[PDB]
Length: 292
Ligand SMILES: O=S([O-])[O-]
View 1 (spheres, rainbow, N blue to C red):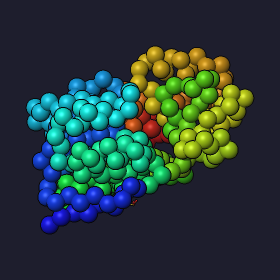
View 2 (view 1 turned 45 degrees about the vertical axis):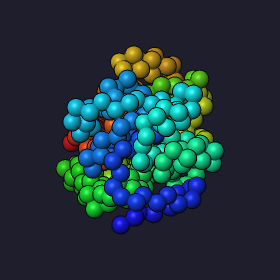
View 3 (view 1 turned 180 degrees about the vertical axis):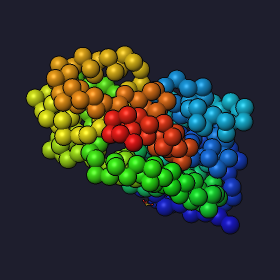
View 4 (view 1 turned 90 degrees about the horizontal axis):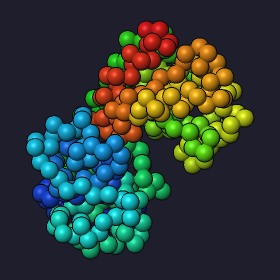
């Protein structure tokens, strides 16, 4: 009956399907809700959503009103203790050896599997959640359905094959474009037949490309389509006002996509519930730029 999870800080034994789950990280609520586990607490990340559950996942709450935790002054260890959980899911929470001891003193705790304390590969997060809440087979079909949905996009748009994409943050950082590097977070673009432009590779800092101002134009001009994870029309305005972005062929040839807030959220969550939103709402935008 008992499930043993192996993670970065040891092993956690879950004796039976959990009844009172805390979602301690930024995104685990999506994968829990997907297998009909409503958390007694969800942790806010951004967007000021009600109960920190974004629209694609909100229906699964079934009217439930979880406590909303935050990481503004670290993990709210005392609030977690007061919720009396029987499982703490803390995969995307910045857990370290010390906070893991604090969480484990309250309840069986599932930490991240590796060197990413935040935003480990989404499928490894989804499979761990699936094991922990005794829904591994259901979670397997939900992962498969995301891959199927993006493959279906590719089947409808064979002309996209080998076109070059970049996935950028919705805001400059201290004057720099910030690109998502090729890795798990860009697999959904490869799934639709695109490639990630290699112009960002020399500018790596951990999992992102921080583009010096004197390289912004040449790096953006390598791509056929640019997806900016803007969260507001003000974000788009500030990107198009940047003198290097403004002077680029990406701007002259209208190769930019500026996401709605919901689409930015859906990419940011990269979950079994959020990726379908991306598969539905991004392709028609790409089609405007590359042609169907
Ligand atoms: O982790 S594999 O499923 O991409």
